[PDB]
Structure formats: C-alpha cells, structure tokens
Amino acid sequence: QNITEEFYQSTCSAVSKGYLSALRTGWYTSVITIELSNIKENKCNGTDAKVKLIKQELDKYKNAVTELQLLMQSTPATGSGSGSGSAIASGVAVCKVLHLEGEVNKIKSALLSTNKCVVSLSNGVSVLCSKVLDLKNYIDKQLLPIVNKQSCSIPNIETVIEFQQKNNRLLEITREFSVNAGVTTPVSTYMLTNSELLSLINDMPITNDQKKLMSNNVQIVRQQSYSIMCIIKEEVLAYVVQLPLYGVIDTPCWKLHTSPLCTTNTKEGSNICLTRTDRGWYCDNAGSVSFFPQAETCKVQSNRVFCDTMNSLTLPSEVNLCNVDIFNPKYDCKIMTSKTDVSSSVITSLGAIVSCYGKTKCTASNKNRGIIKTFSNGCDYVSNKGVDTVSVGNTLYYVNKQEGKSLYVKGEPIINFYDPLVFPSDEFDASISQVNEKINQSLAFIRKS
Amino acid sequence: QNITEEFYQSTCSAVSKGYLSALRTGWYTSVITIELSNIKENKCNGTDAKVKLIKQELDKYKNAVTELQLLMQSTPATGSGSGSGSAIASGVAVCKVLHLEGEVNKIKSALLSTNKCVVSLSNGVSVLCSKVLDLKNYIDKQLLPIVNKQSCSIPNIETVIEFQQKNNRLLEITREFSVNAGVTTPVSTYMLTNSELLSLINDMPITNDQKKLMSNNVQIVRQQSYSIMCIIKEEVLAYVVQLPLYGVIDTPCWKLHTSPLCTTNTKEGSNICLTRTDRGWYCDNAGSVSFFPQAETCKVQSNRVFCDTMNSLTLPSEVNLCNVDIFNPKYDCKIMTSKTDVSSSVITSLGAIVSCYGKTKCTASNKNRGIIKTFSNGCDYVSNKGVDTVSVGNTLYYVNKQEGKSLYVKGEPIINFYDPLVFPSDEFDASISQVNEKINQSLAFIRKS
Amino acid sequence: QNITEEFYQSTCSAVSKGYLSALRTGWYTSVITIELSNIKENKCNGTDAKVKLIKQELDKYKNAVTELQLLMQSTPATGSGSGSGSAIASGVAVCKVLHLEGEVNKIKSALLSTNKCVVSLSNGVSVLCSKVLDLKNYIDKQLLPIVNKQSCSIPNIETVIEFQQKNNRLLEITREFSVNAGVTTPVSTYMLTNSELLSLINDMPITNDQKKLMSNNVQIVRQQSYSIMCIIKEEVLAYVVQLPLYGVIDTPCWKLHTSPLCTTNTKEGSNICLTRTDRGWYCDNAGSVSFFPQAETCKVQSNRVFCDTMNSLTLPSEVNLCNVDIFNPKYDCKIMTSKTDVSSSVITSLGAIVSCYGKTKCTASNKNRGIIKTFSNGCDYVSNKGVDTVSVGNTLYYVNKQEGKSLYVKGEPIINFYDPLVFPSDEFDASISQVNEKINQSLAFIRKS
Ligand SMILES: *[C@@H]1O[C@H](CO)[C@@H](O)[C@H](O)[C@H]1NC(C)=O
Ligand SMILES: *[C@@H]1O[C@H](CO)[C@@H](O)[C@H](O)[C@H]1NC(C)=O
Ligand SMILES: *[C@@H]1O[C@H](CO)[C@@H](O)[C@H](O)[C@H]1NC(C)=O
C-alpha cells in the first residue's frame, strides 16, 4: 500500500512498515520428462560431410545420455545446509518413487497423446507431468533411415541444423547438472522455459489471485525453485522441478534497521556504545512473527516480501514492543554493547540512519544543491524527501527514491541513562534486563565498599 | 557402512558415526592445450554469403585469441582467500615454467603424433599433457585455400557449420576466463569434458581403487578442481587443470550437531543457556582429528565425506571426549552461553534435535498420521523412524530418510548443575573449566560478603 | 613498486606495504541499445524445411521480447544489500528517465547514422549510447519478404544460419536477465563484448593514464560493474551498464595480517590468548584511511588494489600506530581475547605467520630440501625466501612466491605482560585500554581483600 517509516532517536533504529507478505511454506513437485532414443551408435560407411555432422551430433547425444546415467547413480542430495535439513526432500521423495517398477511407464502412457497430464503415483502424490522435448520421435523418424542400413542415407542440411537445435537443450541440461551434482537453483530457462513455467503456474490447483502472484513475479519464483535430477530409464529422462508454495499471503511485514548508539564525549576511550540486535525482516504469521535474520533470504518486489520460512525464527508478537518501548517487560529486547565508536550509515527504505562519531565528516546532499544537512556526533536520521546521497567519511551512499512518509520520533538516546563506570561494555548478545542485572550486581559490589 | 547416531540429552548434541573419509591433501597438475592458427585475418574481395559467414566466425576467433592474450598478461591469481594462501599455487608454479623458452615446444613435440603424453618439464614435474581441440590443422587445411588468394574460394556449407561447432568451445573457454580473471572452479565441461576428465583420471599414476573413487564421484571431483589460464605462445593455448588428490582415505568421520540447552522456568529473563561449539565434520587423520568448521567445505556422497584440508583445524583425538564425558579434564570442551531462549531445530543425519522454549509449538509428524510427538520445553530428539517432518513455530523441516540406527543417550541436562545467580551468561567462546573458574571466582566475591 | 613486509613478533601480526590504490568512488552510466523489429508473427502456408527453421527462430525471438517485457515491469532492484543501500541507484536513475516520453526517440535519433554518440537526457546526465545489435534492420530487410505475403518466399540457408547467429546474443541476454531479476554482475561478454567495453573505456571523458588503468584490468572492471535492464519501448531494447570510477588512485595501501598470540604453559586451561582485530586492507584516502574488512571486496593485480568504497569504514590515520606501538594513546587499538589455543597459519604477502600451540607439529619446508624450520610454541614467522610450503598439523599451505624484502621486527610477545588470574579472557571486541581498565577495576576488588 502506502510505505511508511519511523525512526526512533532513542535507540538509533528505524522501522519500515506497509509491506505485504509472501512466505514460502510448501512445495509443488512437477515431473519434467524428455523422451529419449535408445540408438546403438550405429555406424555405416560414409565420409559425406553431412553424414559426419550427423554422427558428430549423435555422439554428443550419446555422451550426454551416458553422463546423465553416471550422475543419477550418485544420489542428488547437496541442496541441504545450515542445520535446516534439505530444501529438496519433497522432490527427492518423488525421485525415489520414480525408481519403482512401472512408474516411468505410467508417465510414458499419460504422455502418449498429450503434452500435459496429472499422474497419480503409487505413493498418492498427484504430480503435474510435462514432456518438453521429444528426441525419441525425432531421432527414430529422421535419423535412423540415415544410419540403420548397410550404407548411410545422406540427410539434408536442414536436418543437420534442426538436430543441433533440438539436441542443444539436452546438452545444456547435462552441463548444468554435472557442475551442480544433480540439483540446481535458480531453475534455468534450459530446465524450464518461461512458457513452460507459466503453463505450469496456470495448471496448478491453486487460487486465481495466487496464480496472478506467481505469474507477475516469475523471476522470484525461479530464484526460490529447485531442479532435481531423478532417473534415466526406459527411453525417458525425468527430473523434478520444485516450485514455491506461498502458505502465508498479505500479512503485514516490516523491516527493522539498527545502528550503533554511543556517547559523544570528546575523550577517546571514555565512550560507551550499544546497538539493537535482530535487525531484518519481520512478518506477521499465524499469531506470531516470522523473523528473517539473513539479509538475502528475502526478495522484495515493490511492496511484497518473498521469504523462505526455512531460515527463519518464530517470535512472539510482543517482539514489536522493542520498537515502541524498549524497556517494557513483556519482551526482553536484545542489545549488543561495545566501545567501538566508528561512524557508519544504514540506508533504510525511506531515508538513512547516520551514526557519526569522532572526527568523521557526515553529510546529506542533494544532487543540484550540494550539502543540505550536516550530522553531529550521535545517531541521527534524514528522510529521502529532497536528499539524494549521504556521505560518511570517504564513502558515499545513495538514498532510495521510493515514495512514502517518514516520521522522526524524537527521544532521549538511552545510552545516556547509563553510568559509564559500571557499564558492561563488551556484551555480545545481551538484553536490556540482562544489562540492568549486571549493573545491579555491580552496584552491590560498590555498596559494601 | 552402517550409519549410526547418538543423541546426548545431557548437552543437547548428537553425533552421526559411520562415514568414511576422503580428504584433499595434494594436487595433480595437468596441462591442457589447444593448438591455434596464426592467421593474419587475410581479406579478399567477396560478398558471397558463405564467405561472409566464414569471415564472421574467423573474426570471433581472432578476438578470442586477442582477449586471451590480454588476459594472460594480468597474472591469474584470485583463487586465494581467508588467510590459507592460494589453492592454485601448485598450478601457478606450472604456468611460470611454461613461460620458459622452449617449454611450449616441448609439449608441441610430444603432441606431434598423439593426443596423450607425459612430459617432464625443466623443473622436474611430470605433468600429463592433452591436446583437446586442433584449430591449427582445421583452419590451415580447410580455411586458408579459402582466404589466402587474390579472390576467395567459396566454401561449402558443411565447412561453415563445422567451423562454428569447432570454434564454439574456444569461445566458451574465453567467456569463462574473462569473467573469472583467469581461474575457474568448478571446472566446466568446456574446460574439460566428462570423457577427457575420465581419461585423465584413468591415466594417472594412482591406485586402482582410488581411480574408482574419482570416477564414481566426478561431479565432486569437478567441484574441488581449478582451471588456471597460463599462456598463449607459439600457436598453442595452454591452461592448467588442478585435480584433487586424496591423501587420506577410509578413516572414520563423524558429524557433530549442537543446539542450545536452556532452563525451562516460566518467568522470562530468569533463564540461562549454553551451547556446545565447534559443530561440524570430524575425520580421523594421521593420529589427530581434522576438523571442518564451515558447513559447505564438505560434500557428502552416501557414506563418503569429501573435504578440503585447506580450511580445517587439527585437533587432538581427545576432542571426542566432549561427546562422551563433557566434564573430563583431558580436553577443555568449548561452550557458548546466553539468555537467548529462542526455539529451533537441527536436522541431523538420522533424526532431529529440537530446542523448544517459551510458548513455541513443537511437534514431529508423520505424513499419513499427522502429529505423533509433542516436544516439551527443553532440548529433545526424535529418530527418523516413523517421522517425516518436524515443526518449530511457523517453520517446517523435512527429516532425512536414510537407513540407520539411532540411540537416545539419556542424561541430566547439564544446564541444571549451575546456579543462575553466578552464571556467566554472555560468554562467546568459553570452555567448561573457564566457566567453572569464573564461578569459583564469583563464589569468593560472595564468600567475604 | 617494491613490495615489503614487516612481522611484529610482539603482537603476532604483519603488514605488507608497497601496494598502490584504486578505489571505486563513482559510476559511469552508459546506455546499451538493441534495435528490435515489431513483427506480428506473420504466418503463411509453408512446410518447406528452410521455412520451418526461420519460423522456429522467429518464435524464439518473439518469446525473448515478451519475457523481457514481463521482466521490465518488475522494477529491477535486487543489487542492494548489507545496509549500504543500492549499488545500482545511479543506473536505476537513468532507467527512470528513459521511461519518459520521447527519451527513447532521442537515442533512436542520435543512433540513426552512427554506432556511438553522446546523448544528453532531459535530466542533465550526459550518457554514452551504443547500438550493439541491429535486429530491426535485419528482420525487416531479410525476413519480411519471406513471411509477409500470401505464400512464403523461401530463404537461403545462409540466411537461416545468420539469423540464428544474430539472434543468439539477444537470447543469452534474456537468459541472464531472467535468472538475476534484471541486474547482473559481473557484466558478461553477452552484455558487453571485450571490443565494446574497450571502446567504451576509450570513449569516456577521463584521463589517459586512467584509460590505461581500466584497459589493462578489464577483467577486474567487469567484476566491479553492473548491467541493469531498463525498458523495451518503440522498437528499442535499452539496458544500462554501470562501470567503475576510480576517484582514488596511487595512494599507498597495506594489508594487515593477524594471528592469535597465547602463552605457552604446559598445562591445558592455564593459557591466555589475545588477537588483533580489523585484519584486512588499508588505503590512504583523503587525509584518513579507508579500511576494507571483508576479504573479497578487494581484487589485487600485481601491486594495485582495486576496492569498492561502498563496504568500507573510514578511520583516522592514527590507526597505523597499532602496527608500530600497540600501546600508544592516540588510537585505541582493538583486540580479542580467548583461551582458544588452537594452532593455525596465515599466508601473508611475503611469508607466513604461524601460531603453534599444544602438541601441534609446525614446520616450513623447501620442495627439494624438505623441512628447514620447526616452529616452537608461540607465534612466529618465516619469509618466502627459500621456503615453499608451511605445515600446521594435517594442513599444508603454499607460500606466495612474490619478490620482496621481509623484516622480522623482534619484540616481547605482549601476552606476557598480563597476570593470568585477572585477565579478561573472553572479550569479543575489546581494546587495549578497555582491557587495562577491567584489570585496574579487578585490581581494586582484590585490593580491599
Ligand atoms: C536492584 O536490587 C535491589 C535490592 O537487591 C532491588 O530493591 C531493586 O529493585 C533492584 N533493581 C533492579 C532494576 O533490578
Ligand atoms: C575453587 O577454589 C577452592 C579454594 O580456592 C578450591 O579448593 C576448589 O577446589 C576450587 N574448585 C574448582 C572447581 O576449581
Ligand atoms: C589504576 O587506578 C589507580 C588508582 O585509581 C591509578 O592511579 C592508576 O594510574 C590506574 N592505572 C591505569 C593503567 O589506569
């Protein structure tokens, strides 16, 4: 809708509100097939140049099949990482079924007459099939009358050119699979062309507005998809495409921006610092909040946030209280402490946080007008209305030029409520109460003395 | 062999045993050559369409050579990172030799009659050579009678098509090298086709079962290899392929899984936490243990672990005592402390650790039966026998479906042996004794008072 | 010039001096155009094989245009990350202008007669234009007399082959843009060939020695560039290439190497450790020092360092005092403390730091001579003169073979100036004075008692 933003001067943080959710919760598994020819590399006596080229491209086909055969032996399972298990388990389950006797025949037969079908496998999963390239019919009808005789028939050059074209796709598929150990992501247009992907989106048992969502964001849908190599058996090459399912849609999302907040004394080493933790994306999800701590797991498209729940934490909705009253007791807001007063900026959705310390030169400029604000020591913020760049020391940053309203929530920097002599100044993952507890402990060790 | 797994309730950790080692310790360097033609871009008067296409593809060849010439000037050396020095130094050493006078002639001459050879260079390294594409013979015999006259001879269309085909590989090689600054990894099938790689594996002075190991895991062999650009000199393009050498084979490996272990009091902020560090892969290696702390440096293929020793630490074998008696004195087991009681799961090899805290909903489900276990606050574990998924808050995880035996080692959670008032609750990289030492120090500051 | 290196025994660190700077501060934006044909996929009755191939390649063209049309709707803006805002804002600004009425016509018209031009847009930016592929003229003059009639004219096979060739580039461009959501980096040779890039470098309003710098490091220039998709409107495909501008040139750069420094007592757990922080690249920049903490943001070419200022911190030049007198007061040198005495090495520019502890076996070897140094417990260093490898436990490292002079600055390891009983042994981001302050605090808690 209408993007908005709040900067909290008291904690050197900012929240961008107004975004709408799209969280991956499930997976559609589709089977993609290429019908192959069982040729025997039949050789006949021929030195005709058009015969050589047909043999040369038939060898590239033979090798492609044989490399895919040595690659399906080695169980494709290297799309797992970071303790979350395998993203691909849904599809690896389908590959296991395909290796069952008569299951390839079952797709062979549904794809006897048509390109699309809905096959139910003997494990109860109703997969969408698709034949995307027919090399069995091509090689068997155009190329065997050419090599299956005592002396070779001579082909026309259009056949030579059309075979190179048709075989190309099989080769690029093999190429990708052999440098990725059977699993790819993103899913390339060789794995699945824009037309085939859009048909597959159109053909799924899902709601029309969610078909619209995927069609309008196909690049993001690709980036969140996998292609898994299954099996080459009985004149069929089969691989599984795993497409994202968005079980959470149109819940509010917001992004937390954080920057270090220090004191501004003139003596170096007399200064204390604190910074809010768990910067990142927060989406309302099923009564709680899904939190996405890694910067890259969320792709943003206008006002929609596409995230994978696989690398997220689930928090109580009280976590939002850290943005309105960082001292409330409902939620133990987490902070980091240091004495590292080094200047820096964070480009937010509608502006920029600037943490300026020491002798660093900190400004915000307009392209035509030059400098229009100078930041003082401390943590400060500027809206993107009328600003194009911000500079901190020798680095220049470009402010985002999105339309929206910022709100500067004034407040005392909470670093000023702390006595520097009893401040726990090297805390890596503490909390507001956990710092007040060590202060109250260290106020007792000075109480007796 | 038979994968097994032990979960230690007392420390919220688990070990997967049964894997077999394959650690990269060395490098084979092979020289890959493409013989080139020194054509002068000879132009003759011709507007015949088949002449244009031959000129168009000869310009793409000329430029390819000239870009590779400007790229070999800039010393290919950007495959170094993280303080470990250069992975590629073995091959960069061979490139330096190749620039010596008469060393290209020496390979020119061994490859006068055959495609394979074993050349000894003037530095005593016995490299495997290989001519993979002959453009000198092709261009000099099919294309100069076509452009080296007053008026051009006209070529047949098969020549046009065959030249595009043969020249393609040179172009994709140039493409790769110019976006990677002379070093690539993985090694693409353009750098080295599956056939050429399998021949090169077959042709090395190594033991037959280790030839088998590499042939059966070519995708992993590629991912651990480099291609380095050397030199274009005297009608030869030469680049070096560095293949992995597995100096450690068939020693036991095991993977440590760790998850946070906290108290389960009902009051928020009254809870302490600890977590074991150095999760990852451990392989027995030459009387010690090679430890691989980064998740991605180890590719797993069935029960074999392929790791690069370049990013590993070497530990005493006593490090395994942390999995059997975390309090023993032989080895100072390392732990992290916090008050971050946030729920999470770790998908292990044969099961799942679940650290459930607060109000988080934590279950394990079977596809057909639905929920079949509910986790309580604390750290717990479930085997993959009869379970397909585990859910923690809004995230769903897929359990691995490998065959093996799990063993639930019951025990008191060691977090319960600690007095929360004297607990060092924000320790980033501590150790069991190092925490007991600060407890014993803080038991003295309360002893006088 | 002459690379040099200093190892500081007192702090287990080393500095490599002698490098020359090249820091990205700005951006050149160029507009790259491909003139397109507005064909209507005109179908006529034809089953001639050469007609099929022309239709097949015209469909691949139609789809390419239509996918690029659905991709330009979704605002290309996923080259932003890590709080630094968008690297691409300079170019996204040009895309916004191009969507203005009559701005595509303005480039259409400057490129009516020539391939190069300098167009001033209605926002005052003087961009370099370029027409790199003309498919409007090709399709309109060779292919419409072929499909714009009642029955199709038959084309020659050279036309079929030339169209495949010319259309290829458009297809690979679409391929790249659709798996990258409209932004690519590095800039591929499909986005911009070496010839086109070198012309664009030659054609910019910049100084001749800086043209030389870019021409001689084109691979690095690519790696630091972006390609952004703009707009398909009025028979023009336009995308923006953003090339690096080096606002800082030929200032001194140096790289800091750091390794843990511990005590060498024989009892495990009685040992304290400290390590200098902020290892990395330091370049003099405009009276301060630009510091590059991430290892990969700086590409090194002989003695030149190419860095992006976007991910850098700006420090006072007094930060160099940490390498000459780590205790000076001008700058609060930052250190990390632990009890993690685990052995390791750092390969420097002209040598190797070795931190050897426990029972670890630590040597430096020469290829022909074998072991030539054995390291003792502590932190030590060896020059690359006469050494080829260094081994720490089970890992082998290759020393860099660059020419230069090392200097071993002897000195007492400063870890020895600390009383282990009052040492803050788990400090994550402390400083020299900040450790002396907690020592002086903990010397008072023992003073009363
Ligand atoms: C600190 O401790 C005193 C006495 O033990 C108590 O009365 C006071 O409320 C405590 N304050 C905080 C903020 O915990
Ligand atoms: C703690 O200190 C006391 C006296 O200094 C000593 O007797 C005791 O063994 C120590 N305990 C530990 C666990 O270090
Ligand atoms: C430590 O404190 C004493 C008295 O408070 C002071 O005289 C001394 O100079 C201090 N030393 C340091 C290194 O701060």
Image (tube, coloured by chain):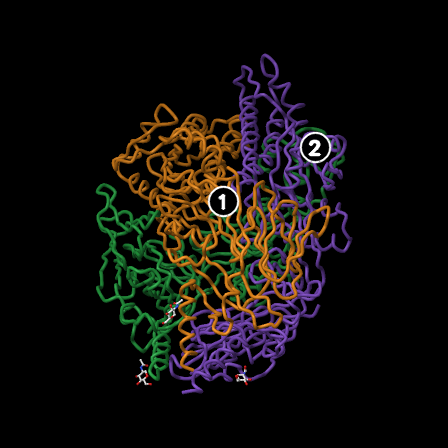
Chain colours: A orange, B green, C purple
**Residue furthest top as drawn:** C150
Residue under the image location 39 percent in, 26 percent down: A115
The residue carrying pointer 1 sits among few (fewer than 14), some (14 to 19) or many (20 or more) residues within 10 Å by Cα, namely many
The chain that hosts pointer 1 is A
Residue assigned mark 2: C103
Residue type beneath disc 1? Lys
Is residue A288 positioned above or below A149 on the image?
Answer: below
Which quarter of the rendered image does ligand 2 occupy?
Answer: bottom left
The foreground one among C258 and B273 is: B273
Is residue A225 positioned above or below B362 on the image?
Answer: above
Residue C357 coordinates in the image, percent (x, y): 44, 78
Residue C82 visible to the viewer: yes
Residue A128 coordinates in the image, percent (x, y): 35, 32
Q: Is residue C414 left or right of residue C420?
A: right
**CA gap, disc 2 and disc 1:** 35 Å
Q: Residue A17, labelled with which disc?
A: 1
Is residue B142 positioned above or below B83 on the image?
Answer: above
The residue carrying pointer 2 sits among few (fewer than 14), some (14 to 19) or many (20 or more) residues within 10 Å by Cα, namely some
Residue C274 coordinates in the image, percent (x, y): 49, 75
The quadrant the C terminus of chain C occupies is bottom left
Is residue C142 positioned above or below C246 on the image?
Answer: above
Rendered image quadrant of residue C112: top right
Residue C290 coordinates in the image, percent (x, y): 64, 63
The chain that hosts pointer 2 is C
Could you tell me which secondary element the residue under label 2 belongs to? Answer: helix
Q: Are marks 2 and 1 in contact (CB under 8 Å)?
A: no
Whether callout 2 and callout 1 share a subunit is answered no
Residue under the image location 57 percent in, 26 percent down: C58
Could you tell me which secondary element the residue under label 1 belongs to? Answer: strand
Rendered image quadrant of residue A64: top left
